[PDB]
Amino acid sequence: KVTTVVATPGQGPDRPQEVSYTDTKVIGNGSFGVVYQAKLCDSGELVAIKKVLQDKRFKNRELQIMRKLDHCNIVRLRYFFYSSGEKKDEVYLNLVLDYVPETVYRVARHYSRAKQTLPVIYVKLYMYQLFRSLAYIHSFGICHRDIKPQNLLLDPDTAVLKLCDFGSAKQLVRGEPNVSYICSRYYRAPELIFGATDYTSSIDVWSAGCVLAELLLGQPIFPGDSGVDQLVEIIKVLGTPTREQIREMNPNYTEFKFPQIKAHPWTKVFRPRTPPEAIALCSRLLEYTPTARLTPLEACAHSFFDELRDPNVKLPNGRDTPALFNFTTQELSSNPPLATILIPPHA
Ligand SMILES: COCCNC(=O)c1nc(-c2ccc(S(=O)(=O)N3CCN(C)CC3)cc2)cnc1N
C-alpha cells in the first residue's frame, strides 16, 4: 500500500513535492498525537512521521524550530505536510523525520536488567554527541526543554546519537515568561522544581547531567514520586542549597519542604570501580546555580571525553568513530577559541 502526499522540504526551498511512502507502523504515543515508522518508496530508507493536530490560527512552534535546525546529532526534518481526520478544523501537521532504530533509554534499560553498567566508551560517545546538539540549539536561543534518555535516539552499529522530540522546545526571548512544569521530571532542574519562570538554556544542561549520572549509576540518580520528592532526592545528594544558591535558582519561592540536610560526597554516590573524569563532569553539570553549570561546548572539551579526541580510538566493534569534529561557526560561537581543544590534530 503506497501513500503519496504533497510535502514541503524541511530545510529546502519552499517547493512542495510528491512524496510516496509505505510500511506504516505506529511506534509511539504522546500529548501531540501519534508517531509512525514508514519507508520511502523511492529511496527505500526508513523515516518517522510525527502527527500532531494543528489549529491554523497559530503556527506550530515545533515546526518553526525544526525548519531552522540541521545537525549531525539531531534528527533532521525531511518534510512536512497536512492531513485531516473526518471533519474540517481537524488539520493534522505531519513531520517527516529521519528514523533512528534505538533509544538511550532502552539501551540503558537492558544493561540495568542484566545488572551491568554501560561501557564507559558508550557513555563518552553518547554524552559528547548530546552536548554538540545542545551547543547548536542553544546558539539559536532554542531550549529543548525535554532531555530524557527516551528522547535520545541511537544507531547501535554506528553509535550515532540523534536528539529528537522538539515538542517542548522553545525560543527563549529574554523578558518573556516561560513556564516551570517543563522537563520530564527526574531530569527537572532545581529552578523548575521551585517554579521559576526566568530560566535559561542551562536547564537542558542539568537534564543532561541527570542522564550522565543515570548511565554511570545504572538507574536514575534523582528519582521521586512528584516534583516535591525530586527536590528531596536532589537535596539528598547535593545537600540543602545555600540561600545564595536559592536566589540564583528561582527569584521566587522557598516554602521549606523541610530543614537543611547537607551534602554527601560525589565519590560515595557512584560505583567505586568507575571514578575518573566522569565524576568531575557530573560535579560541573549538576550545580544549583544555573550560571555555574558548564556550557555544552565547554562540556565537550572536558577531560572525560579526551579518549574520543585521540586519533587511534576505535569503536568496540572495530569500526571508526562517527564524526566528532565537524563543527560549524554557529556551534563554536559561544567560545570560538575552544576549537583549540575541540578539533584535535588528525585533520
Ligand atoms: C514526539 O517526539 C518525537 C516522537 N519520536 C520521533 O520523532 C522518533 N522516534 C523514534 C523512535 C525510536 C525508537 C523507538 S523504540 O521504543 O526503540 N521502538 C518502539 C516500537 N517499535 C516497534 C520499535 C521501536 C520508538 C521511536 C525514532 N525516530 C524518530 N524521528
Image (tube, rainbow, N blue to C red):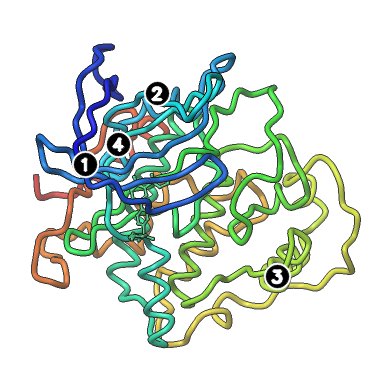
Distance from the alpha carbon under mark 2 to that under mark 1: 17 Å
Residue 319, image x and y in percent? Answer: 9, 64
Eye-nearest disc, 3 or 4: 4
Determine whether label 2 and label 3 are within 8 Å by CB. no
What residue did someone put label 4 on? 76
Eye-nearest disc, 1 or 3: 1
Determine whether label 3 and label 4 are within 8 Å by CB. no
Residue 39, image x and y in percent? Answer: 20, 44
Distance from the alpha carbon under mark 3 to that under mark 4: 36 Å
- Three-letter code for the amino acid on which mark 2 is drawn: Tyr
Q: Quadrant of the N terminus?
A: top left
Q: Specify which label sits upstream in the sequence, 1 or 3.
A: 1
Residue 7, image x and y in percent? Answer: 28, 22
Distance from the alpha carbon under mark 1 to that under mark 3: 46 Å
In this image, 317 relative to 70: left or right? left
- Three-letter code for the amino acid on which mark 1 is drawn: Thr
